Every structure is written in structure tokens, then in C-alpha cells.
Length: 142
Image (cartoon, rainbow, N blue to C red; front, top):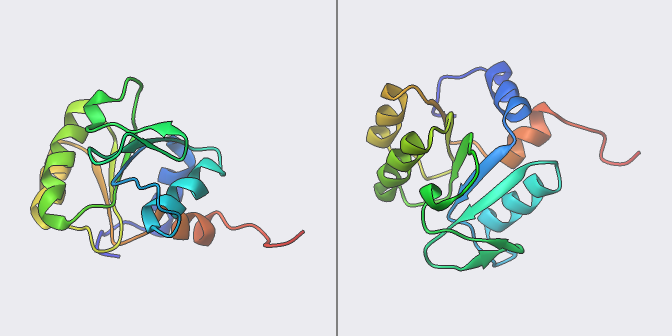
């Protein structure tokens, strides 16, 4: 992890916030963004795809910006190149999100600091799916 949170904090984020805006969503089954999104949807999360390059992902309308999402968003999960993250962070702030989650290889210091300064929590170099499995684990077969 790049962030300085504890496993307890991560656990809290995953347990308390169910409204997710997944930036960089993709329809390709083999893409990490698609896998994580499906996993979250299968685990009671309300996931809103965000990508200007696509019009819908996993049977959900996909927006160009998180601001275009009608409903409340608590977590903005990033699947974007680091140099592009600032944009989504500014939008996350405007949207009133609570957390900005930088998936692997998406972290960009300046963007993270801006979010932090605005009051948002930063999760970095972690995977929402991997953390869910690690922290809110369940037996693989019952």
C-alpha cells in the first residue's frame, strides 16, 4: 500500500460505503476494471461505471464524468493513468464523495494531496476486490 491507513480503516471503508463510481470501467471481461466491478456488484455494492470512451458497462449506463451520475457517490475507484487522476479527483470533491481509491499503478501524489486537502480519505495501491477478500473474507466453499 502507498496510503498510510490501517487494515481496520480499509475494512471500515468497504463496510460503510456502498455507493461506488468506478472510473475507467470497461466491457472487456479480462480487464481488471471489469473484474473488480463485477465482483463489487456481486457483493452488494451499487456501482456506477464512468468512462467517456464507452456508453455502457456490465449492463449499466456509463458516464463521462462522476458529476453526470445522478445519485450519491461515496467512493471513487480509479482505473486510470496517474497523469489523468487529478481530473477525477476534482470531480470527486465536487460530487461530495468521501473516498478516492487508487487501484494498482494509478496513484498520483499531487492528485491524492488535493483530495486529502478537501477532506477525502485516500486509499492507494490497493484493489477493492483484493481488500474485500482479505479483510472481509469468507470461506471459499461451504
